[PDB]
Image (cartoon, rainbow, N blue to C red):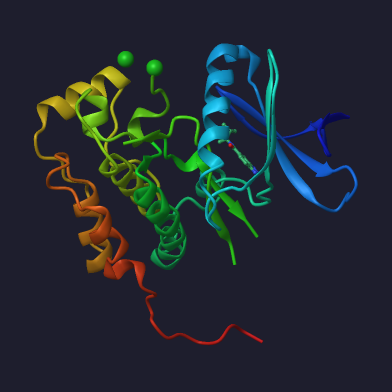
Amino acid sequence: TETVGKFEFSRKDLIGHGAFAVVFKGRHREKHDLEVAVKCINKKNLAKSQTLLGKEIKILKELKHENIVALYDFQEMANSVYLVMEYCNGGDLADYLHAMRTLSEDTIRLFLQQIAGAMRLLHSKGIIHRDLKPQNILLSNSIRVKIADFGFARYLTLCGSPMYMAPEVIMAQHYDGKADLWSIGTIVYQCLTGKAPFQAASPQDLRLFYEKNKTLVPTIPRETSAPLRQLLLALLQRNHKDRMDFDEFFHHPFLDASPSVRKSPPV
Ligand SMILES: CC(C)[C@@H](C)NC(=O)c1ccc2nn[nH]c2c1
Ligand SMILES: [Cl-]
Ligand SMILES: [Cl-]
């Protein structure tokens, strides 16, 4: 059993693994029923991992929201760094989509309302996440959504998953918070259809695709509701000048419950 301050964990309880972090389920050492997640360095990418976890500490100290993973404690050592965080017991959106294949528009609305709340705070603070993808949208059991993985966040060297990155980011142009809105659009599209809207054989081929095609239109199924169709077209604008801004996103009709009134749940 390893310890970080008043918290402990076994590496048997591996719950997350990225290029730049390994995450374990843990517990409070005094209150054994208090579950946590302990985010550690990935030694395969030590230098970068250390840098990113350091940055994440600094960002999350400033960010407190019900839809952003909470930071409870942290320790920074010479060759290692540890973040003690809110445990999310429902895995991530990547696992969920693999299992479900596609989500109902109602489920999408439920998750996106929560994302939108978190993003509202980022917007106010002038923070861009830059690495939004299904792997860092965490679920917790009434499914709560929490945005994680803030190591790449900046106030107004990125690597991750180019299929979720805005054209201006891929093309090494100026970007702002609207780059996160593109990412959200791609995620929403994937929840709806099971696939990313724009794919290529390689990151370089995706760049070439975005460079060549000054108008990008995602293929939205005929059966998609008018509000969701409109939202997806506006989020997935190639040129950020044309892309929906945060205000318009936050107040979009799709982010209101449909149906507005339903049955009370089965007894
Ligand atoms: C695997 C990493 C690269 C990343 C995507 N996961 C996390 O940062 C993470 C953070 C807090 C959590 N609390 N419960 N589960 C969690 C997972
Ligand atoms: Cl690559
Ligand atoms: Cl490439």
